Amino acid sequence: MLMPRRMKYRKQQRGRLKGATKGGDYVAFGDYGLVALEPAWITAQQIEAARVAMVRHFRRGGKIFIRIFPDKPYTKKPLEVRMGKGKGNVEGYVAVVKPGRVMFEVAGVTEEQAMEALRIAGHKLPIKTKIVRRDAYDEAQ
Image (cartoon, rainbow, N blue to C red; front, side, top):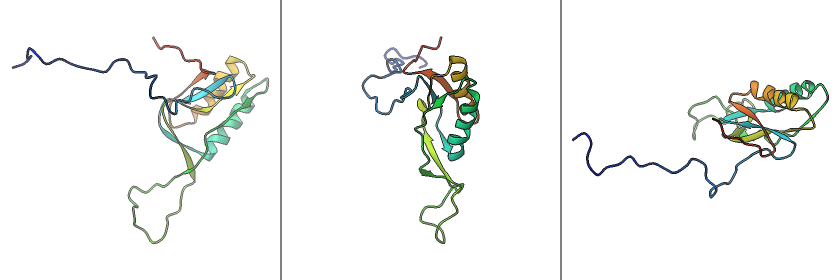
């Protein structure tokens, strides 16, 4: 028996879903928005450090809107559940992100300056990020 006469490769229909859509960041505020296509932990510096590079990038000035904030503890210890002599030294705080999360968003600046600036922030990020307009998402051929 290699190929029965009843079984069939079944799969889901389409990838997107209009029903369950709780937490789908697109842009929010501004004209553009930097989305994180991968899960990662954004440090405090990544938020300000990246913003500084972006603000300076805009040759014709510009303003950025940040929503991500460090809250989730950042420890380099694999196991530490109910174990320890008190509490280990935390290596700062980070902001957990997921694929499709707008961590940044600019407005007023040109597409070239905005797209590049938004990229500069993701350049130093530990995940992939792309530029998108206020709810501007096209298909990828």
